């Protein structure tokens, strides 16, 4: 029922470029938003929980911010290992809706 | 930290075949398990929550069962629209770990 609008759909950047992805929730979800990284053919892995909290073992180049309806995920310096599709997911209410994903490629 | 072991990794069946997928949690998670369907290039969509509860609008050919550490997802009669990768995800504890996925194809 909550709708999650994630943009851009895809982007290419160079090694060391800054990447920023946004998600917009159709309802106020406070900070109940996760960010996942899904490498090709692999399962999504949780990078950031509660909008801004880094999971253990996750590199500092990854960050999240926002609260309410607007949220922003940033890769400060893109590395080869970061080529993936990234997703937000709200978990305030059923179903726990994912954003449509952002495919990150290196130019 | 919880580990989710999903099998098989991939399967092909015929239209109308029965498909069954299993997930095993490394810790007791009672019924705090979701199942998602991810079509190629799309976000995961929630089909089943709390191990066995169908989301609104989801077809009856989809079901889930289990509690504790073993869970089973079944497509009773495979249709063309069901070609997707399916995932379990535990949400009892951080990080909310996904199983490795099962790619379902039609032979």
Image: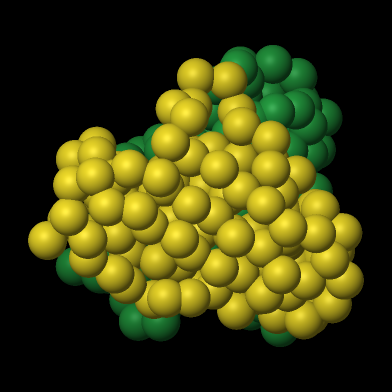
Chain colours: A yellow, B green
Q: How many marks?
A: 0
Q: Nearer the viewer, residue A24 or B77?
A: A24
Q: Residue furthest left?
A: A107
Query: What x and y, as percent, mark residue A96?
Result: 73, 61
In the image: residue A41, left or right of residue B1: left
Quick check: B38 above or below A43?
below
Q: Nearer the viewer, residue B83 or A94?
A: A94
Residue B16 visible: no
Quick check: A13 above or below B41?
above
Residue drawn at 67 percent across, 63 percent down: A71
Residue drawn at 44 percent across, 56 percent down: A86
In the image: residue A95, left or right of residue A34: right
In the image: residue A106, left or right of residue A10: left
Residue drawn at 80 percent across, 53 percent down: A32
Q: Quadrant of the C terminus of chain B?
A: bottom left
Q: Quadrant of residue B67?
A: top right
Residue A50 visible: yes
Q: Nearer the viewer, residue B39 or B83?
A: B39
Query: What x and y, as percent, mark residue B24?
Result: 57, 27
Residue drawn at 48 percent across, 40 percent down: A62
Query: What x and y, as percent, mark residue A22?
Result: 55, 68
In the image: residue A93, left or right of residue B47: right
Q: Quadrant of the N terminus of chain B?
A: top right
Query: What x and y, as percent, mark residue A30?
Result: 87, 59
């Amino acid at each position: 029922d909550i709708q999650m609008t994630q943009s851009p759909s895809s982007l290419s950047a160079s090694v060391g470029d800054r990447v920023t992805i946004t998600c917009q929730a159709s309802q106020d979800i406070t900070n109940h938003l996760n960010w996942y990284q899904q490498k090709p053919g692999k399962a999504p892995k949780l990078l950031i929980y509660d909008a801004s909290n880094l999971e253990t073992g996750v590199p500092s180049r990854f960050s999240g911010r926002g609260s309410g309806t607007h949220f922003t995920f940033t890769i400060s310096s893109l590395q080869p290992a970061d080529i993936a599709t990234y997703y937000c997911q709200e978990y305030d209410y059923l179903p726990q809706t994912f954003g449509g994903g952002t495919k990150v490629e290196i130019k």
